[PDB]
Length: 385
Image 1 (cartoon, one colour):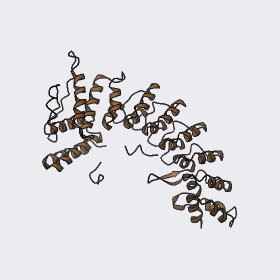
Image 2 (cartoon, rainbow, N blue to C red):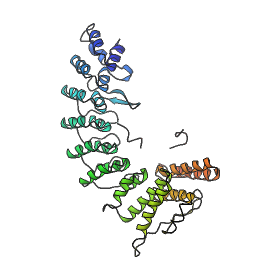
Image 3 (cartoon, rainbow, N blue to C red):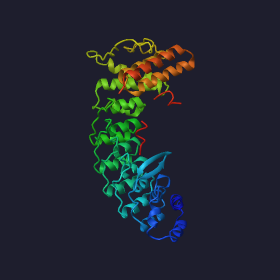
Image 4 (cartoon, rainbow, N blue to C red):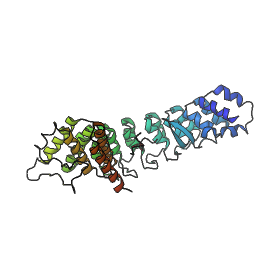
């Protein structure tokens, strides 16, 4: 019975439901409206799929399913506890949002992950819904259960207009998530040099997160050269922080971009800064010990130890593992990840001894620095709406 009233609400057939709602009274017309049809409610599905004409009629019958959290689907994943206003926002259904609000829907009702209607419109970038929600008393600084703000997710998805608008309306540029992440990091991870420049217009301070990473280092890990190039001349970064970032960027060039000539370019830049002031030379730190996994290798220490490298791809591969463990450390997932990557390439090429040693080392790293896997494979946090 009601399983039929709801599948026409989802699919949007408005003529059918009007005749099924003429063959029943106004007291039980509310019981079918408060359905459990595949976890959602007739009013929720009516908002997720933008059926404005039928959402307005659904509400003239009973405005009591209006803050109900049910199940919705986006990008294949499924979201629990999403109210209808939130879902109308994530989908871009601007006029469904306006109608939902004119009938007195809370602009502050979130999903179970505590994602506001405002944050939902920021994900896919619906600027006009964002403006409307802000004008209807949305709170710029309610974040999800991880502390990811609207401004943050807007920077991560590269939405300059929306990020600008949120800053214009007074959003705090220096929020830290629970993991210590700031909107400046989301600019770094997305290569949004534009939005990074705009955040700096509001004196955005450049900090480490829980993992110890600055945006400058975060841009090096994820490989966005425009950020790393931009920040090697920003006065808010020190000399050895520039050096390390260029050097770590080189590692990303060797292992992530598979580009030895790009890597040497950045390693040379880093080398010059190290040996630019002869009265204070930045020597490479010296690890506790040589590592079998790294073939007992040692980081280059002079501009000329860099020249005889390009004809030696293996030394560069071992340089990159060394540089990464030095800068990122054993706790950053990229270190073990690229050790295992490296081991895998060696397996493919023939030396299984190199492979197993790298894989053994990575497991001892993954297990000795404790609080991804090979089967799993046979960041995701920020794509949460």
